[PDB]
Amino acid sequence: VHKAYENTNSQITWKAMGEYRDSFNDIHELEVMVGTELRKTWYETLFSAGYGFDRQTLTTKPVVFPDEDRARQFPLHQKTYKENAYVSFFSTASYSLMN
Amino acid sequence: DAVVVTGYQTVERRKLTAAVGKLNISDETIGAVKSIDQALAGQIAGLSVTSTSGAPGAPAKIRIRGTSSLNGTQDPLWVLDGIPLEGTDVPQSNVLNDVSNIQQSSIAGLNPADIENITVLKDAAATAIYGARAANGVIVITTKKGKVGKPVINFSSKFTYMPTLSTNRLNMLNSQEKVDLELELLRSNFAYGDNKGGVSKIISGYGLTDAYKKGGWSALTPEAQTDISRLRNTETDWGDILFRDAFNQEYSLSLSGGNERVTYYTSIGYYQENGNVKGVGLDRLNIVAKTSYKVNRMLKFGVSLFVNRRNNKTYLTDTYGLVNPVYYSRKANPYYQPFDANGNYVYDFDVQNNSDTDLGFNIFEERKNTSNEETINALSSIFDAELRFNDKLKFTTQLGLQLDKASKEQIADKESFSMRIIRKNSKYWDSASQSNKYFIPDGGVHKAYENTNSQITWKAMGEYRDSFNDIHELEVMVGTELRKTWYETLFSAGYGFDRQTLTTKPVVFPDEDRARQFPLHQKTYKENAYVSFFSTASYSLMNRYTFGGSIRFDGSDLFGVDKKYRYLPLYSVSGLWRLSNEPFMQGTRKWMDNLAFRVSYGIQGNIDKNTSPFLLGKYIVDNILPGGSEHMIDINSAPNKKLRWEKTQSVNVGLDFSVLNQALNLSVDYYYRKGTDLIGKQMLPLETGFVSTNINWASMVNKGVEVSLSTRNVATKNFSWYTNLNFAYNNNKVLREAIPEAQTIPGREGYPVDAIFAIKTAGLDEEGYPLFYDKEGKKVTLKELYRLQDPFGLGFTVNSDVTPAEERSFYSYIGSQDTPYTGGLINTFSYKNWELTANLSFNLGGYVRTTPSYNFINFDRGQNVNSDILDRWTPENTDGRLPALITSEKRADEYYWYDQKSEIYKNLDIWVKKLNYFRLQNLRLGYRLPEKMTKSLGMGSASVAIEGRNLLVFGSSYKNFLDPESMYNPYAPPIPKSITFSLNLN
Amino acid sequence: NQEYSLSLSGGNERVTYYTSIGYYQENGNVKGVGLDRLNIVAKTSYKVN
Amino acid sequence: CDSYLDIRPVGSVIPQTAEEYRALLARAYLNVPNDRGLACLRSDEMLVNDNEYDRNSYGDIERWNDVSPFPGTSQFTWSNFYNVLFIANQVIESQKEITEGTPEVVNQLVGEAHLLRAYLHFVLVNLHGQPYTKSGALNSKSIPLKLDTDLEKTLGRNTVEEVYTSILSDIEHARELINKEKWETVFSYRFNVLSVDALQSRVSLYMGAWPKCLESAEAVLAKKSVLVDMNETPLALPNHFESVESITALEQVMGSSVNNAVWVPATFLALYQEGDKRLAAYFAAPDENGNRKSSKGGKREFSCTFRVGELYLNAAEA
């Protein structure tokens, strides 16, 4: 038996934020950040099984499952795909007084 | 410049004893190309670049000094920063539809915006340092580098408009003449397929198929006449349904620089390129990160990283391309509307080249229900270390790691023609039911391909440079190289697939052969290793006589273990004589800057990677006595312990000549390269144990002239004009090759690799059949030519005593598919801030065997046809020049001889056409913004450009085809014209 | 087991650069179990204005 | 950075182990041509049937029609002989490279290859070479000796003395290398020490070297001399592979097509005098013309290369 698994995990993240930092009367300090983030993730899996496989010859043999129930415990080809997307808007504030 | 990069050394121009062609890369030189293999067309003399397909990402077939092998590697070797690249070979097959799925070379991953120079090594004196990878030439890629000083940043943005593909050159029938042709065929006795068509179905649905044949148009009821009139009045634009105009994008941001110890370079580049066929697209995003540090006055370490990701979307077609939209633009009926009045699908049942209408094809349905998507992840990392042991002695080591991973995914839903053909091909005879069933489950198919191409290379060379008595100079290099390559592929298919549920269904194959016909899981693994030891020497005397030489011992697991051939040198001896520096010629120095004569000799090598020196066999079960199951091995391929590289003996004579302060430069090279021991199939003596096998026995020759002339026509403070003419003629000829005894077409021995042999015809007789020529030069028929005999009189029982060796004399040599004369002319004008570059290319002297516009025995009336079917011979039109549609009524013997030998009609000289085309490869007008305006914007420089690619093609006529490079393969899109607007900022 | 690492770095008033190449080979206590890793890092920060 | 040049391709069976080379040599054994039946068709013990198809193939061989045969006639298999010779030479050259095998197994494989090569050369020089005992036939070129696996050379015909010297050398090599005493009945086509001695006896008999022929025949008889007694089992064929007399059952001398197309001429049967059980055991029911068919071949279980009766005859002649 020769079983091949191929799992790809991809992600794209994009952050964009802005900071404003000010000092008032030499005793107040203000720091305000406002930003956003768009993220996206993909996870793909492929599985391929070949029975009757000869290691030197790389040749397999056909399989005759009795029914579909017995074809799921000995799978020959499986594909899974999962894609998600996230959108976030964040902000932080800080105020320091007399240190 | 003043130096040449050969991938191993840096050779001064004044000490260059080899044929080398350089091309500096910029927007003003190559244009807005997206692959660098496509920017070399007509820019280097002796380097012929041809387009295999017009689809995005299609590799270009490149030949340096002609074809150097028969059954081995024929593509050049690409060297990136001293490390040779892998996966650059162009896969060549027979099936014309394979261009639909041709793999992209790794060259498509290198951004031309990250490359400074392209150096092509042509002759033995330049290529022999590459050992057994030199017979096909070497193209050395020099990538851009950080320049010492303040950081430099570039932001190029190119926007391309691709005009729609106009099928007006296809010369196809509209509804009127198509319906007229169908009616006239229904009247006549030509009945190969009479169930097919649009008129035939309409007439036969009312039971008038026999009344029409006897009476004609009047014999039809008005119910059957209004339908035919509606067919005549229905016109469909298949160049609008299938093809589109496109807006392509490209962006590149390159920031570099350096200081006294570290030089750095970074670049990002993303482009989106659409195809002229709807649904075809290709994205490429790449990153380049170079940085070189000087550890000490002796040590110097650099790291270069190239990361690439390409994404291809395209259409799914059958094995034989009945769906192919480019070819379907020639099959779609003019009166067939894909949608009915209610918007429902209308299926095309005439899509099969056979007489069976059961599988319907709708282009919209296939586009919606099918997909072919590939993703390529590529990486190339080069770590180069250098140790300056002495002022004279230096050492260099270099490690290059390359990895390409292609993941392909083809999905065909249940309601699509691509699945219909699969299910139909799954037809088997059920023994227990006395019927025909299909073993492929009812559902879609999901096919997955995973190809991996890996390479690791390690080079280590020591260079010595000394000068004695101020007139002697000696340069010696010694080095070694270990290189290992892996190519692993995996294929997996699942039938019964549902697109959303992602669930397949079990398949019960009746036999093992039918299981091989539909593979479900395949693995392939190739691994090779190469060990090379090379050396190079050069001696320059009085700055006037340079004598160079090189040697390279190559070993690999693809060669035999025979000690007689194990490590044989691959050498070269070169020589340069600068006639301009001679004391007796110093009088002619007020106008002559250079006159150098260079000669070269050497032996190159080629590796046939599809041949193995091992005993490849197969396991069988048999026995020599009753009972018992002995496991036996049957030899598939003979073990060849004397397997070795295909030798190539090259002699090159050169001449360089510059006058009037570089006002006129001329580089002429005459080359003669005779190849021996080319790996090919030979009919062995019976005492060798085998009838025939692949050994090193064939022969070949190439010879010709490369001329490169560069001129500065006008040199004025405001207006400057430069001309660059590259010309190359190659005379290819096969000297010794073997053909099967059953083969009826002549062999190429004495003719080029792509020789075209065709049966010369004298025209037609009074009945419209082709007329041939006998040995005496008189016009004969097929019956006289082949001496057909029909004793039984049944017609289909014909036979001929003409032996294949005599049938080979019917064909005559026409020409060669590869054009002997190739080259280009580049004109550069500069007027103040304006800069206009016009790069034109020519490929002259070729021939192409085009598919017949119609078959005179197998004409399918259910599909459209070219406008020359109306110039065929007809009883009512006896002045036609093309053969008439023949039947078995008049001459059964000739008809059945034509039928059972389909190559006679395909190989007629009327289907072979000249191939001489000039193409305006590039026409770019650029404007450099004034310095004050750029300074006002804070930019060091700025520029705009408007550019036209493939705007003009002229020369020999290419009628019924969309392009002269598209005259051979109907399944490949033509080279698309484009208009690019580019903005560059610094 | 054997691990190697080469970290080259530096910078100047406008551009700062970092590079690293590492390779380790490790074996498990169970025969036939092993794991190798080749790592490359390339960072460059430019001060455009 | 990685290179050794020792890589075996994956995707096809490349013989490296002793079992794989045994499979290769077994395939060589299977493809041994049975051209001695066609050669004896040239003799006086065979008569082709009066049919047309059965005579258009074997008629010209029987008539000694060397010049202008019918193009449809049967042809001697040069190709099969030299293909089996190639496989034997490949097995011989692959010694010191056979993996996963006991030295007593690798040595037996190489000895079997040597003896098979010697036997094939002997049969070829017998078919297409002048007899060793003929005057002026010692220096005459007969067949090209295949002693390597080279595919890029053309072999010239070797003289009969050279061929027989090579045969004797290969017999000596097989004697030094073969170490199996007796194989299984189902795998009895392979060569053993008795096969070496029997082949040496037959070779020396054909050369006329009576001393060595007698020595080898007596060695075989001392090691094995049990025969099949015809008087206790009338239908006991001595050449049957399961009989106690067969030493090697390599080649089925009589093919199905040739055996189905010939009779035994009445003269040869008349040579059998009254009281011979071979008369009623070898052949079938008499035909009206007086020529019987045969039952000693035509099927795979009648394969016989050496047997003890031939050794008795060789010993008596020497």
Image (cartoon, rainbow, N blue to C red):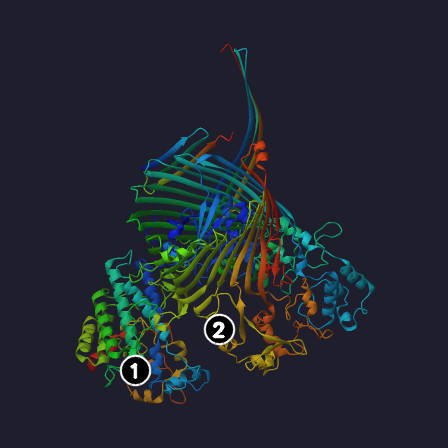
The residue labelled by disc 1 is D277
**Residue B326 x, y percent position in the rendering:** 62, 56
Find residue D286 and report its image quarter: bottom left
- The answer to whether residue B899 shows anywhere in this view is yes
Q: Are marks 2 and 1 in contact (CB under 8 Å)?
A: no
Compared across the picture, whether B192 is left or right of B10 comes to right
Residue B742's tag is: 2
- Chain letter of disc 2 in the image: B
> Tag 2, which secondary structure?
loop
Compared across the picture, whether B425 is left or right of B652 comes to right
Q: Residue at x 66, y 74 (%)?
A: B887
Position above or below: B871 against A66: below
Which is in the foreground here, disc 2 or disc 1? 2
Crowding at label 2, few (<14), some or many (≥20) Cα neighbours within 10 Å?
few
Query: Which of these two is toward me, B288 or D188?
Result: B288
- The answer to whether residue C27 shows anywhere in this view is no
Residue lying at the far front in this picture: please name it. Answer: B587
Quadrant of image for the C terminus of chain B? top right
**Residue B9 x, y percent position in the rendering:** 37, 49
Badge 2 amino acid? Ala
Position above or below: B295 against D253: above
Q: Residue at x 76, y 60 (%)?
A: B231
Position above or below: D40 against B591: below
Find residue D37 and report its image quarter: bottom left
- Chain letter of disc 1 in the image: D
Badge 1 amino acid? Lys
Query: Which of these two is toward me, B581 or B480?
Result: B581
Query: Which of these two is toward me, B270 or B311?
Result: B270
> Tag 1, which secondary structure?
helix
Q: How many marks?
A: 2
